[PDB]
Image (cartoon, rainbow, N blue to C red):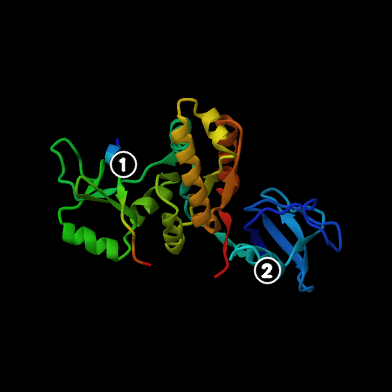
Amino acid sequence: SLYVRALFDYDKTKDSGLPSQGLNFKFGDILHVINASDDEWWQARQVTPDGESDEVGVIPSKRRVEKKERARLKVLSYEPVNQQEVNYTRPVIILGPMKDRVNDDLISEFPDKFGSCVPHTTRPKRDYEVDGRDYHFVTSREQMEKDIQEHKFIEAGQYNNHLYGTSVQSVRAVAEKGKHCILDVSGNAIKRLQIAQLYPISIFIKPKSMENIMEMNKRLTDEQARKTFERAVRLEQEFTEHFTAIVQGDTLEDIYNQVKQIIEEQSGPYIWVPAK
Amino acid sequence: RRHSMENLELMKLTP
């Protein structure tokens, strides 16, 4: 049958021209499509982490959703998904404002279910550092670079003219040890992990406003709040298709609780993945 | 730690 991840938000009340009672959903939701026949509207049911809703509603077709979206600018509708079995604990990528706090809280509050991978660096090992503990210390920039071009790293960067990178093997190492690897990385690492058959749980924290940002962090100035909100907008525009979920709240506590639940809901041995 | 990772200038990577 056809199972789909919703890449956008749908509100019945907002849409006119519905043939039957619609089914309104949120981004990230998984929908079971009962009949795709009409070239306009589809009949689907919501798929919950617990059950499968006994209900039916009308959702716009992929075709319909796209014409509407394309009509504006001078396209995200539905991502077909399959249920897949995993032998590993999925990595976790939180993105958006407050993500760092959310990362710190997961590791602190649940040390057994969460952890950090060992990154690679070309920075010369200090006498007190142990290779394999702090970093995997690469003794050749040439080698480090060849590793990068060969896609050994899901992310790489520079600090004080030293190369740093986050290895796939290194992430897979925590994943197989039974912990969610908490990654501080950009939206680009998401696809690489997927390509690597390690499917991260990717959660974006979407600020409702600049005020929303300022309320959760009271020590930010207007300039900072403005900047923080503006980079969250482009982050969302760039990576949206690659998010497993998007969360909003009026408080950090509210956001955090949601991420804990989503991670829980996404942490089973069977997960929904793109069909390809 | 890890401080250096906290601040990095990221590099674009090949497809």
Q: Residue at x 78, y 74 (%)?
A: A37
Q: Nearer the viewer, residue A94 or A221?
A: A221
Q: Disc number at residue A37? A: none
Q: Name the chain under label 1.
A: B
* Label 1 neighbour load within 10 Å: few <14, some 14-19, many 20+: few
Q: Residue at x 49, y 29 (%)?
A: A217
Q: Quadrant of the N terminus of chain A?
A: bottom right
- Asked which quadrant contains residue A39, the reply is bottom right
Left/right of residue A6 with respect to residue A42 in the rendered view: left
- Asked which quadrant contains residue A133, the reply is top left
x then y, percent, for residue B6:
33, 40
Amino acid carrying label 1: it is: Asn
Query: Distance from label 1 to label 2 (Cα)?
Result: 42 Å
- Asked which quadrant contains residue A184, the reply is top left
Helix, strand or loop under label 2: helix
Q: Nearer the viewer, residue A175 or A24?
A: A24
| Whether marks 1 and 2 lie on the same chain | no
View extreme (right): residue: A20
x then y, percent, for residue A234:
49, 51
Left/right of residue A179 with respect to residue A149 in the rendered view: right
Q: Disc number at residue A67? A: 2
Q: Please determine whether, in this image, residue A234 is positioned above or below residue A32.
A: above
Q: Quadrant of the C terminus of chain A?
A: bottom right
Q: Is residue A95 visible?
A: no
Left/right of residue A58 with respect to residue A266 in the rendered view: right
x then y, percent, for residue A249:
61, 36
Amino acid carrying label 2: it is: Lys
x then y, percent, for residue A235:
48, 50
Labels 1 and 2 touching (C-beta < 8 A): no
Circle 1 residue: B7
Q: Name the chain under label 2.
A: A
Left/right of residue A6 with respect to residue A139 in the rendered view: right
